[PDB]
Amino acid sequence: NSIQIGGLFPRGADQEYSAFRVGMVQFSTSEFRLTPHIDNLEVANSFAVTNAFCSQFSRGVYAIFGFYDKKSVNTITSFCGTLHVSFITPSFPTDGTHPFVIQMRPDLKGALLSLIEYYQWDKFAYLYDSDRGLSTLQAVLDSAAEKKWQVTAINVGNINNDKKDETYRSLFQDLELKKERRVILDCERDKVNDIVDQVITIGKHVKGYHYIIANLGFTDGDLLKIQFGGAEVSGFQIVDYDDSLVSKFIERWSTLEEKEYPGAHTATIKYTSALTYDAVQVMTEAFRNLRKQRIEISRRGNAGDCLANPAVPWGQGVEIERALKQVQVEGLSGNIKFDQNGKRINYTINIMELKTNGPRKIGYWSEVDKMVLTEDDTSGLEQKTVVVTT
Amino acid sequence: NSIQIGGLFPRGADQEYSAFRVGMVQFSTSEFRLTPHIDNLEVANSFAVTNAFCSQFSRGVYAIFGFYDKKSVNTITSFCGTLHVSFITPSFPTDGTHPFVIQMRPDLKGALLSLIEYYQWDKFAYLYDSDRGLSTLQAVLDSAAEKKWQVTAINVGNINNDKKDET
Amino acid sequence: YRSLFQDLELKKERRVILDCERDKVNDIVDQVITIGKHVKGYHYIIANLGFTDGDL
Image (cartoon, rainbow over all chains, first blue to last red; front, side):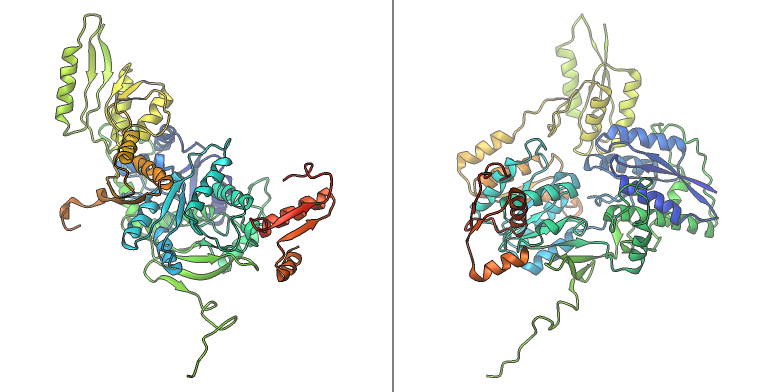
């Protein structure tokens, strides 16, 4: 039983495509086989997104999948909201509730809030890139109202690569006027690298400074460059490597030849690709749930124009979502659950700290339990509580 | 020499369309007269936007006119940039240098910062709707850094109208 | 290297004269970068004619 689905991907997202095919291999079943429709179009062109979308709609695919730009999110929400076509996504969570918008990336901001609550910062700089969405900034500012924080947010993503240099030295010099010791970066994997590099060159990775890297790729980042600077560094990890299923994933992940699956022949993996690999599992789990519900879904693949007026929804697709959010299985990120809005729920994220020996977990942020310190920290290994009689 | 053009007026903007009619009256000329393709569709719905857009595109209209949402801006920019079709809007300006884009609103930003400098303020709240975009926010914060300003921005616009009083 | 400069910390040295060939010069400099001991309050003296020849 072929089951056609979409397969949008940004170019240069090779690791995700590789892990995607890995998902196709790992979870293939005799009962039916998925029929991906790969499309390597840039997400920057919303029109091109429209093109691929109508294209797969012509394919009559029962599902569509891919990344999206903040520039593109409104388009996907508009169409999938209109045509009642379900759409899973690794990308950052939608700022607004929408139908047919499953989203693999857990909300991160609340954990960030609790994280600040732990360090009890009163004031700090806050760098950010626009591309993931400014909503996090809106959050930290709203908190800043209640928490009387004097945050100094600044965008950095406008800067050209060609002059990507002095702009930083000018920037951090500005931070010196406030003598900031505390900054939360909020940038892309690459921008994280360049920023850390410039911090190295200016030497502000010395003890007395501190940093917070607002993303799931904290372990993914190459932090070895600054491990010894004495400044403390901490971030987030959706994917524990100590997990059994994870280590098992690594056992084969390293093995794959790069020629077939480039970027895969490594000890680790980007969390995003991991979310992809999980997402395929979720999809296939849903379709497995369909036949058990014995619900026919054999819609015509000749959907015709997506621009057709009226754009009548095909109800079988509408049925699909009803199952999709109800799905629940383990993945590389661990357990996953969804709200009626398609946002992830009941997720828990592993707070991380870099240390001289290497990076280490210290606690986990539950959706309800918020920050929770581990058992390691709360002990007497290096130092414990002393009873003073007086 | 009648000349086909687009028409994309969001619902509930009657005064705008009326003004458009007055514009059609004041500048009508024998050399040519415009042929509007007026439409009343939700600005928020990028899908419907694309629908009417491609619809007029089927007309092959030599120009298009209408507004856009901050959500929809990427749509129309992506199209005029791709389709090399000219377009004009009275909506708030794009943050980027987008080809085949015309826009009637001069940026209020520099005048705003200037006005700030005139009062020589140091501390202020900054209430904002999301809808016109956060560019002014990025700007006022930018000037805030160098000027040692203490901004207190807040997103009032997400509040539900059902209880738009308690908040 | 890290063991080495840590030893310098016991004397809290702010002042060091390197005297090495340009390759090991560059390496030691890189390590100084990684350990971050190139902030204000430290100083260095590179004892060779290649002071411009090396990256700085």
